[PDB]
Image 1 (cartoon, rainbow, N blue to C red):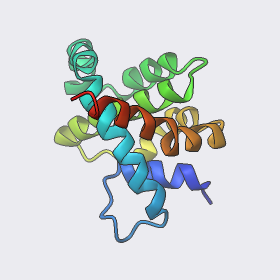
Image 2 (cartoon, rainbow, N blue to C red):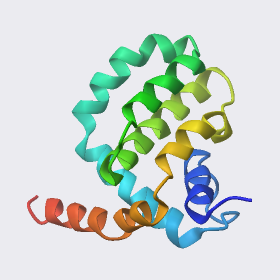
Image 3 (cartoon, one colour):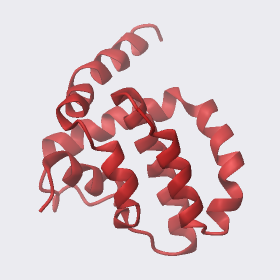
Image 4 (cartoon, rainbow, N blue to C red):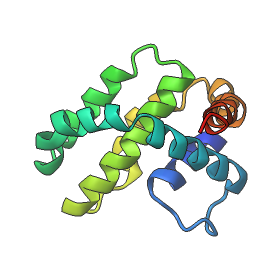
Length: 138
């Protein structure tokens, strides 16, 4: 049995058809949040795919897992979500080699998903605020 936020994160990472998704309203707002981060952090993630390329193409799951866990030490909600969307991309790339579930990164996700009120709060308040601040400035 999974908490609300964890359920949504899985459905996001697993790219579930939003129809068999049990937490629609959050999944919905979660990926809108990630989408903006993906736009905004694009140069940063370009660096990250560069250093991770070997671990990804070599399918070194272990290696990827303690990278992300390291990056999560004492993470703020901003960071929790930045890391999440980073993991979304990796899972999409790993999916090219072998089928890879969100379940394989349960430990990392537990990290992303701690302080769930704080995190849900970000998805629903600040993330919205940021996205708008940004788009009103072109």
